[PDB]
Image (tube, rainbow, N blue to C red; front, top):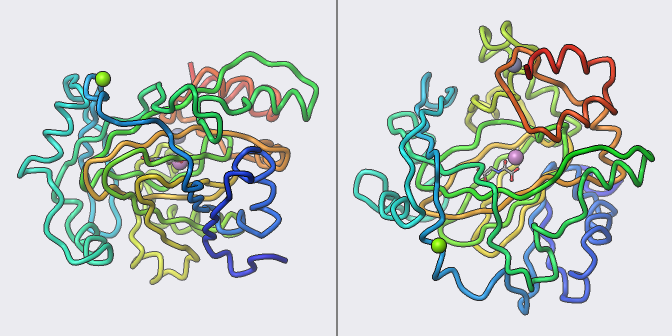
Length: 331
Ligand SMILES: O=C(O)CNC(=O)C(=O)O
Ligand SMILES: [Mg+2]
Ligand code: NI
Ligand SMILES: [Zn+2]
């Protein structure tokens, strides 16, 4: 078996290898990459997402989210308070203000120490889940607005035509903005490109060990667990690397820099934080190997997780027994 310790793998495709997206994903999996839950892909040196980022300031963040924490430094939840609309130029100025800017630090490890010590004492503002793309239409390779759709994959593998669409989303971050422990909707893959700015640190649990993370989360968030049988779908819970180590949970970490892609694999729990002002683009995708994960994915039926129009069809076709109860949650 390849990559039996489930380490995060880093790939450096040539421009020739960067032509065929599906083929490269299948290659990475042939080397065991999926066992980690997360891989990094450094694009060929000749490739670019677009010519410049000079003209993005007028993108609107219609509903910036203030991420307010509760709990202890290593075990906390966050709630998202809605704020008034602002442009990306206005958000960048806010991220760079004395109140929100990255503190002085020695290196990424020192900054990670400072994040886990101090995150709960601040409420950074995140622009999340903004439908759109920053890839130039002329970028033909690994353009996250031009991928094969999940509805087309399901149709190709299973023969069933379904409604729904698959588009990318933009993320504008600042120091301490946080993504909670989660897998993707329907345990899909994700791909994330860091277009510009400061890094993003990721933590990930190997898919084969995801249930260990779930059992710890039920112990650490016991009222949330009683409220919902898949409460990590709410995307609110954080657990630090120190707490994971104290409880024997297998995980890995890596820092993504501007210009780099990350891929998350089916049922790879992940969480992380931004180092300073940045912009990322991400989308879900599927492969043939995903189908069985989609059939087994947990679902939130308490009604908190509330997700896209296109997830309906996935549940209806892959999980017809759950359909009924999951849609009672979504209506
Ligand atoms: O970058 C972010 O805030 C969160 N993104 C992801 O969870 C992803 O790409 O799967
Ligand atoms: Mg603009
Ligand atoms: Ni994700
Ligand atoms: Zn729920």
